Length: 70
Image 1 (cartoon, helix red, strand yellow):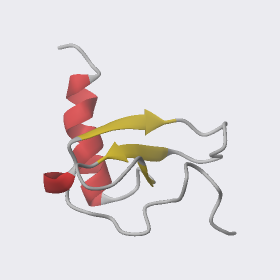
Image 2: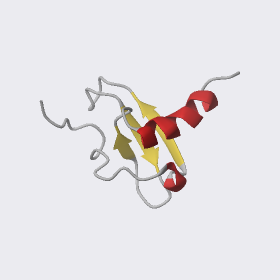
Image 3: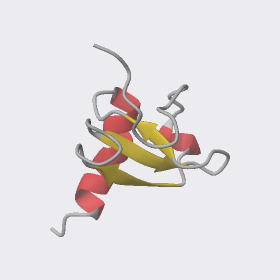
Image 4: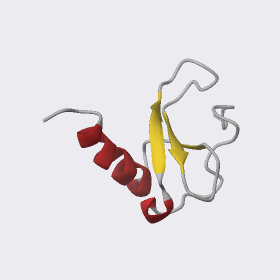
């Protein structure tokens, strides 16, 4: 096992969604072989955070209802 070369660079530091302005979902196939969360904080470029965290899943969660009509 080893860290892949997903987006620019994996989320070297998982920050709270309180600093996440925007984000998107990243599929496992392209430059990434795994799932990652293309974060777009207000003080950090496109961040790639694997959807296996509490902070990530929290940000992706609000999105799960956002990118899913109900």
